[PDB]
Amino acid sequence: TVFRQENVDDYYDTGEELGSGQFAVVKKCREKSTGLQYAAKFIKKRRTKSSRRGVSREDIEREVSILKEIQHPNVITLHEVYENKTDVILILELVAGGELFDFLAEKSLTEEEATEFLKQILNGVYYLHSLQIAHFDLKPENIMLLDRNVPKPRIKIIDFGLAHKIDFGNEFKNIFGTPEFVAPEIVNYEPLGLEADMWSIGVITYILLSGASPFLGDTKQETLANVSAVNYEFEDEYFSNTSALAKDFIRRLLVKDPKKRMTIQDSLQHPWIKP
Ligand SMILES: O=C(/C=C/c1ccc(O)c(Cl)c1)c1ccc(O)cc1O
View (spheres, helix red, strand yellow):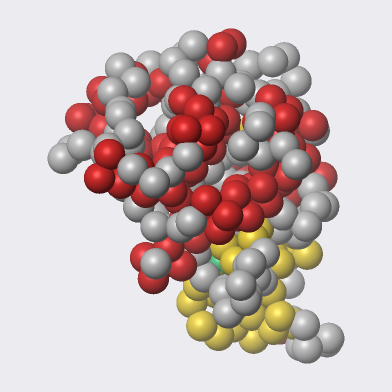
């Protein structure tokens, strides 16, 4: 599938950089014809078949195909896609209130603050899972706020670079996500489904309530070994005034067997969440 091959600079002006990774950079931008503002994600293309630099066209097309399907308050909206010899450029909804990763460093959250964020994450994931889309990269870096200067900020899941359609209940591919947040089946290179996202939600919830990462080791290999062994505990110093029901919610997500883990619907009916 081909994208718009006019020069993006003829239609947009770019500004502040919003983020930067191994194969992508995201810049704030403004569409010349409308004055509306967006985030432009420049993805470096692979230059040869057998290369390890850049992103394969199959991977780029999968991300675009998923973004084109989704429209929900808690996920980004794709506006346009351009390309040239070097890059695919996704023009995405601008979310300018900063990361969930940065806003937490300003403050642990109370259970009310945590559940206000968490309920929005669960709503966005409920939408994705209803469409059989696994995100495969849920972590604070990928959760951003629309406006951080309000008491209950609204959030959006802002990237879909590892997301996959799960039309057979599982997909058998390597997911090189962040060790602290990936489920045991990712660590063990097993078939992957929607359940992997629910594990990641459990990790996010643990961090929201405590400020501490449940599986983090001193090296990536230690973190991955901790995940596979489900080597985590609730430290009293961090959880002494956290409710038992909040711990129960986490405990039912950080479950090695994906079939025994809470689903997204289970998580919305769990007594900590259900109104
Ligand atoms: O920084 C990133 C995300 C940014 C962002 C910020 C505001 C927005 O509205 C939108 Cl859509 C995205 C990023 C994404 C993918 C990747 O591979 C590497 C990265 O660094």
